[PDB]
Structure formats: C-alpha cells, structure tokens
Amino acid sequence: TYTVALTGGIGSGKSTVADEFAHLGVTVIDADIIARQVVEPGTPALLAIAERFGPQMINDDGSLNRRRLRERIFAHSEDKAWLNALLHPLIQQETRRQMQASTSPYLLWVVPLLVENRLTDKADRILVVDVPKETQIERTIRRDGVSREHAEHILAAQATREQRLAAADDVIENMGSADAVASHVARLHDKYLMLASQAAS
Ligand SMILES: Nc1ncnc2c1ncn2[C@@H]1O[C@H](COP(=O)(O)OP(=O)(O)O)[C@@H](O)[C@H]1O
C-alpha cells in the first residue's frame, strides 16, 4: 500500500498532524501508540508486568504506572530485555493487523527517527512536520516537564532541522492558526490520493 512517512523532531507535532490525517480516513500506523495499546488496562502484557514486578505497576485506574516501570528498568537494566521479549512480538503483530485491516487509499506511518535510522528509502513519500527550534523547545518543556537544557540535549541527539527538511518531499509547518494547518493537511491528503492512484496505475 502507498505509504507516506511522517517525521519531525520532538515537539514539532507529529502526533497532532497525524490525527488530522486520521480524521480524513487515513490509516495511521504509530509504533508509540501501539506500544501503549498492548499494555492497556486489562491486557495480558500488563498482567505479566504486574505479576513479575508487583501490583504497584498498576495505577488505581487499572493503567500501567509508567514511571514505576521506568524506575525498575533504570535499577535493573537486565529487565529491558525481558520487557522487549514481552512487548516486541505484540507490537509487531498489532502493526501487521492494522496494516491488513486498512482499506484506505494510502497509509500514514509516524516514524520519529526516519532520518536518524536511514529509513528514507522505505516510504513512497516523506512529510516533515516543522517548527522553529525555539518552538520545539517550548512545546517539549510543557508536554514533558523537562528543563530547557534537557530539551536542548534531546535536539542535539536528533537529526538537525536542516537534515530533516533536506530529506522531505513535503513540509508542513505546525504554526499559525490550527484551521490553516488542517487545511494544509487536506491539501496534502489530495496530493497523496492522486499519487496513490498514479502508483496503482
Ligand atoms: N500548533 C500548536 N501550538 C501549540 N502547541 C501545540 C501545537 N500543536 C501541538 N501542540 C502541542 O505541542 C506538543 C507536541 O506536539 P506533538 O504532536 O505531541 O509532537 P511530536 O509528536 O512531534 O513530539 C503537544 O503538547 C501538543 O499538544
């Protein structure tokens, strides 16, 4: 299936823009979403986490206490492999289920490290969500509760803005009025529908 890879630096708006494509009926594949899905309240993988590490892994609302799990892996690095062995097969399986169940003309794949992991060849098109550096910093501080200096260290561990823009086929700036960003998404959606038809012919 025709595939558009959505990338962008931390805090630029990958999740936000992907939701607007979803609203237009596009199947959105996002491994970070799938990872949360596989440990939702009541899931066997959440039970396995709690049975191993303790009931303190489950919040009063039945959800995974993510901080407590991060604390466990921080204290016991060997438990990272255990967690991977539990979750990786479930994430792969759910990724494939979502691909197979899709009936949309194209797929949107949210790929945070597309440039950093050299995956530019896998998708038919690359869409970069862009914002100024100061905007990434401000939005990451607010969402994630990190210092500005911490945000700068994350940016320094990611591809540069210039590198992402150089790899992009299309750029969406997640700035200005939200209505205009959504209209930009609708314009790109039409472009992708037409490219998907061209590829299918
Ligand atoms: N146009 C905007 N103006 C201000 N904040 C925004 C805007 N778009 C998204 N946000 C917020 O910015 C943060 C990062 O957006 P998100 O889509 O999660 O980025 P990413 O997935 O690229 O890390 C979130 O807290 C989100 O609510």
Image (cartoon, rainbow, N blue to C red):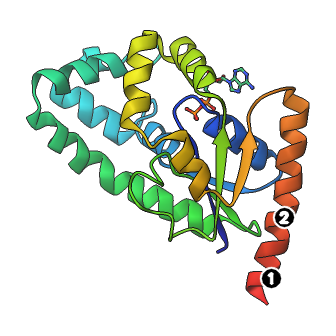
The circle on residue 61 is none
Please name whichever residue, 74 or 57, is drawn nearer the observer in this view of the structure.
74
Question: Please, is residue 127 above or below residue 19 in the view?
Answer: below
Q: Amino acid at mark 1?
A: Gln
Where residue 190 appears, x then y in whole percent?
88, 62
Badge 1 element:
helix
* Residue that extends furthest to the bottom in the rendered view of this protein: 201
Please name whichever residue, 99 or 74, is drawn nearer the observer in this view of the structure.
74
Q: Is residue 75 visible?
A: yes
What residue do we see at 55% from left, 40% from top?
161
Question: Please, is residue 67 above or below residue 184 in the view?
Answer: above
Please name whichever residue, 185 or 53, is drawn nearer the observer in this view of the structure.
185
Assess disc 1: are there few (<14), some (14-19) or many (≥20) residues with their C-alpha within 10 Å of its C-alpha: few
Where residue 110 appears, x then y in whole percent?
57, 50
The circle on residue 191 is 2
Counting the numbered discs, the total is 2
Left or right relative to 174: residue 57? left
What residue do we see at 43% from left, 21% from top?
152
Question: Please, is residue 119 above or below residue 24 in the view?
Answer: below
The circle on residue 198 is 1
Looking at the rendered image, the quarter that the N terminus falls into is bottom right
